[PDB]
Amino acid sequence: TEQQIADIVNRTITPLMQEQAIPGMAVAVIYQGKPYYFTWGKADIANNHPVTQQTLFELGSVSKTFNGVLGGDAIARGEIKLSDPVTKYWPELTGKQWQGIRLLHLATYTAGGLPLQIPDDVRDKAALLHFYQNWQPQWTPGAKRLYANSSIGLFGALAVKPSGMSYEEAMTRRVLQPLKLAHTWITVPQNEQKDYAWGYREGKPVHVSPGQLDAEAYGVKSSVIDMARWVQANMDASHVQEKTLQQGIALAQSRYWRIGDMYQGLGWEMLNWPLKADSIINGSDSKVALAALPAVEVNPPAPAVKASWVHKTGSTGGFGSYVAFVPEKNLGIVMLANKSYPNPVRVEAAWRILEKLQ
Image 1 (cartoon, rainbow, N blue to C red):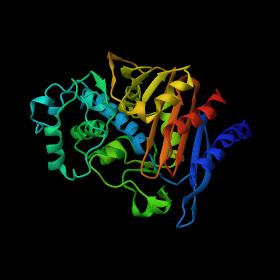
Image 2: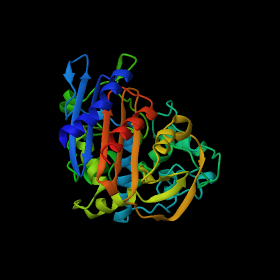
Image 3: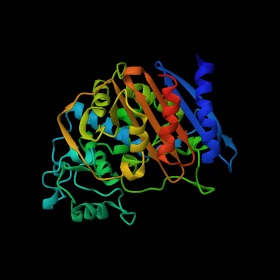
């Protein structure tokens, strides 16, 4: 029942926003394939705008699951293969160290320790090229997973090239438009800006700043309604008319590597359901989530498993989001807030809501 779910979301989101000092939230809960929407707080303190179902939040690394879907959609079209060398799509990357690294490795953060970020002095395509040319691997490709923006950023920029559009256009025309994601953007148009929340890093209003591969890595903004649709679609893509995007969705959740009790999809991450909360709650810690961890290959990739916890966390200077879903259960949650908080806290919270409704 709706009052029940509402009670559930509220017993948890109320103390969360009070203790984490979060000005503004929106969650959606997918409970038996149906979405429920909840809104709190202000999106914008200085312009006095309440959070609504249209407010746009920066998603952070959740932007990376649109990256993997778009990649998969490329794969389904036959324009790319994860086994393809990277130099096939960027032949200017000469340099013996790039020899043997596949799209797969970029995509799944197993290239060899590509660093978490592109250094912020790297400001145009020449510098980026020079950055990749002189990059020296810590490890052989395929041995360790080090989570990175400079890795899967490059997957996404290489993944769209056959299409003949830029990633941003490919994303919009090949994912967002088909899925009726009218409030989801890389670049927010001027006439959508009224809806764009501000983020808050120590009382100061912030938005993600331009950087190389931002759209591919962390540059998506979206409303709760879109995100709730994104979750419903990636949980059950059975009504996706566009066949390459349908398949692309499935491939996003194929299991490509094992790192402990986690299996690395393309942007999404999964674990076997049922599980124990300490899995996802501890694994959500920066100490672990950002660690270089041995990675066991799963070749060929297991198709997508219905009995999974599928999720992604993401955060910017001023925003924290989380997305999770259990295909077997038809159950998911979206959590969009305009202040970052610790990810353990954000998973603990999702788990509280979802375990109460399992």
